[PDB]
Image: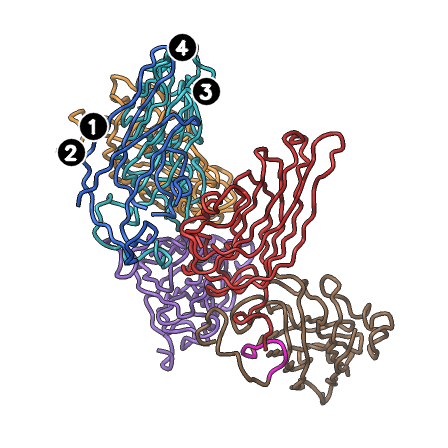
Chain colours: A brown, B red, C blue, D purple, E cyan, F orange
């Protein structure tokens, strides 16, 4: 921001953002170049946002996430994983209510096998789901890398400790992702660009 | 928008000046301002301006050391003054207020006063009936400003400082007064 | 303003750091008299001492409380808890 | 009163940006400025102005890990650039300089250059004749300024930043280059 | 100083002080309300000067002491110490060449018994000496508390570490005091006000 | 026409070593064995003005072992010391960082210069071994504290000594140096 003094004045005014935070709706990417397994792909989307005056940071422990913008290409175009084929990807974007120390499991967290909801003793809240179907075997093979873009409006987040630190000092109203495969093979090489501007 | 005070949209941050101290008969001096230095952190300030919302004084005032049962029955009078300017360090108490231990500031010094308090610890022998008293007080106050633009100590202020003096009323020194002083602003 | 409420420390000192009042000079007078001689008593002190300007602000035909820049005055100090000193001084200012 | 440079009568203080790092083929990025934050201490600054007298680059550049004997014979080209302004963080190297690893800055980017260096570590098998080289260099330079008046990080500068890029010339990554970088000013 | 910015500008110019330091010739008292023994009264006169922007402090580790101004009243006027009487006080203001950790001894430091110089294996430098003779017994008793004031010009001092700390981090060109009694009794209650402005 | 101090003969006191080092430190107070005496391997009084240090030396690893864990180099350090503390102080706790460094910020000891020696010998050639280093190196004055005929323990201001440093966890370096000081 032009001429921090040390936080910005001339902010101070009308802007259609959110209730609590006031500043420039600063983007923090959580890019991944990753994959998953059948059981879990775990991504706390909030881990990189630490204390700083910069425009990929925060001031204090209070967020109001305006929107999560999920880019991503989900392929299996490695030279293997043409056998044991036809798998699909179900995305899960959950509104969490508290963290239990560090990042938790998934098959020990959501109720049943891969088409489910959170357990009855765990009500964590859900926001929405997605789909991605990559079906490629042999002799065509007709399907591969799909592109997914989504605007997705969301709401506020708070941290616990006063650290310029990692994901472990979260508190109430966390939010994160789970990715799920539906077959015993692991073809899915899903790399996602996740913009949060707030 | 803001309802705090007419200056700070800032987070109304607490900076506590805890003491584990005592006094003498003449003076117990406590500047309660340079606890805040300049910084981006949450026990700091931005710029050189305050509006102290309230001073919250906790404290236990005892004499329960194994000595100071003789020369007993002393009491503590607190003084919370609105200062108009310092020069150099904290000026000492009997070199600033007028008369012996039941007084006001001098006629050539008008520093302003806000309020007073009481604490009576009377313990001798064969009961001894009185000891450590607990004092809590909400106390609303107003603005403070520094002149010198340093991330520094107490010697460099301007208009409206404020600080404490503690006074004993007897030649012995039984009073071991430790006070927790929250300022959130 | 009273003396110990203005100068810094106990009886061998200077003005305080928050008070810089200026000093011109000092003097000495030692009267040591106990019993069985007693060898010392009344001492005589005369001193020329050149000085400079003084101004009042308030335009009254009046007392001392109403001055401005460059006042000047005296302080006398004893160094023991007894008070033997009966010091009577004749102070001429001609200007 | 004193001969240093046309700005600072200050103590010509050293702030060292030691690294125990490495690089990749594309980029090794090192802003050598936000080592200094605002402070009264002797590894800091007063205000928002520098005149860097000299950068003194120590460093040992090896590949003496038990791997990276195959895909061998790589060399290191150093780049010490005079920057004209940053925005946000340090912009990455191949997204800033023109062509593949023997180049200059792009035509749409004129950032200024000061000088280059060399370091050739060629070690394969059966001798293997070359390893850790030592490089020391006096290198006189000039002034640096911050815009944003924070006691803070690197993202908040103005005119005349300066930083380093390190470049490898082969697809393997053998280079474990650790450098001690004194700036006294 | 009026309007530190954060050290003072408009200093910058002609002032008859000393070579190295530039600022207001700031006073640091080392007042004592102390006494001595026959062997030693030890006073490192530099201990309180720590790092600070204030006018009883320093910037960096370099001094040029302009003058030491020694006030002091040296008495024996306690109700005891009229017997074993007639003692005198010899002052010693030494230019030290290095500290050995913390403050050292005196009878293990100066050569001989109470009328001496530093030892041949120790050449610490001397600046000057003083005298104070308090002779009081019974039936007059003719002498008591004497007043001593002295201008005494001196020169530069340096510290070792970069601490805002005590006397132990001194280096070359230290300077300190020793006070000496000349009789086995200890009547001397010497309290001294020691101004250093530099 | 050579000396700035006194018309004595520029007497040689040579601190030969047949030694080695470790990775952390090779410590050599070079002014150690200079005691009071009439000979030219001695001193008159307690005041020196070292004209030059002349460093000879062959730095090898040609023992039948230390062909593995190879390719190490030697960095020399010739420091102008400011103050002593009895015997010789630490190296790794005195100079700042790991083996490519300067003295620490709380220690400013002065430096004069550095040197290099690269002995890289493994197997199947092995191409490098014992190197010879000679250096004229002009320097300046040294003072002793006591008037004893003593060793390095009784120093004062303006000492000077050497540190040798290896850069690998093995210890191949068998560095023997002939160090002439004539003054």
**Mark 3 neighbour density, 10 Å: few (under 14) some (14–19) many (20 or more):** few
Compared to residue C45, the image places residue D116 above or below, namely below
Q: Can you see residue E12?
A: yes
Mark 3 and mark 1: Cα distance apart in space: 66 Å
Relative image position of residue B120 (x, y in whole percent)? 66, 43
Q: Are circles 2 and 3 on residues that touch, CB within 8 Å? A: no
Residue E102 vs residue A168, the one in the foreground: E102
Which quarter of the rendering shows the N terminus of chain D? bottom left
Compared to residue F40, the image places residue E23 above or below, namely below
Mark 2 and mark 1: Cα distance apart in space: 9 Å
Relative image position of residue B170 (x, y in whole percent)? 58, 36
Compared to residue D107, the image places residue D139 above or below, namely above
The residue where tag 3 is placed is E78
Chain ID, mark 4: E
Q: Which residue appears farthest toward the left when viewing the image?
A: F1
The residue where tag 4 is placed is E138
Q: Are circles 2 and 1 on residues that touch, CB within 8 Å? A: yes
Highlighted magenta segment, given as a residue range? A17-25
Mark 3 and mark 4: Cα distance apart in space: 13 Å
Mark 2 and mark 3: Cα distance apart in space: 68 Å
The residue where tag 2 is placed is F2
Say whether residue A21 is magenta.
yes
Viewer-side label of 3, 4: 4
SS under mark 1: loop
Viewer-side label of 3, 1: 3
The residue where tag 1 is placed is F10
Q: Are marks 2 and 3 on the same chain?
A: no
Residue lying at 63% horizontally and 67% vertically, measured from the top left: A61
Q: Earlier in the sequence, mark 2 or mark 1?
A: 2
SS under mark 2: loop
Chain ID, mark 3: E
């Amino acid at each position: 921001a032009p001429m921090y003094r040390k936080p910005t004045m001339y902010r101070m005014y009308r802007s259609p953002d959110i209730p609590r935070g006031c500043e420039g709706p600063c983007k923090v990417q959580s890019f991944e170049q990753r994959d998953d397994v059948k059981h879990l792909g775990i991504c706390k989307v909030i881990s990189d946002v630490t204390r700083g005056p910069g425009l990929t940071h925060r001031v204090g422990k209070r967020f109001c996430i305006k929107s999560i913008y999920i880019l991503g290409k989900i392929w299996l175009d490695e030279t293997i994983k043409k056998q044991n084929h036809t798998n699909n990807v179900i995305f899960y974007l959950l509104r969490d209510r508290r963290p239990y120390g560090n990042a938790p499991q998934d098959f020990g967290q959501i109720f049943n096998m891969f088409d489910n909801e959170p357990s009855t003793a765990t009500i964590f809240q859900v926001l929405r789901k997605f789909h991605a179907t990559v079906v490629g075997g042999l002799y065509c093979m007709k399907e591969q890398a799909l592109v997914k873009r989504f605007y997705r409006l969301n709401h506020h987040v708070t941290y616990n400790h006063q650290e310029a630190g990692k994901y472990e000092n979260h508190t109430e109203n966390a939010l994160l992702l789970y990715m799920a495969c539906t077959h015993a093979s692991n073809p899915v090489y899903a790399t996602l660009k996740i913009r949060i501007y707030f």
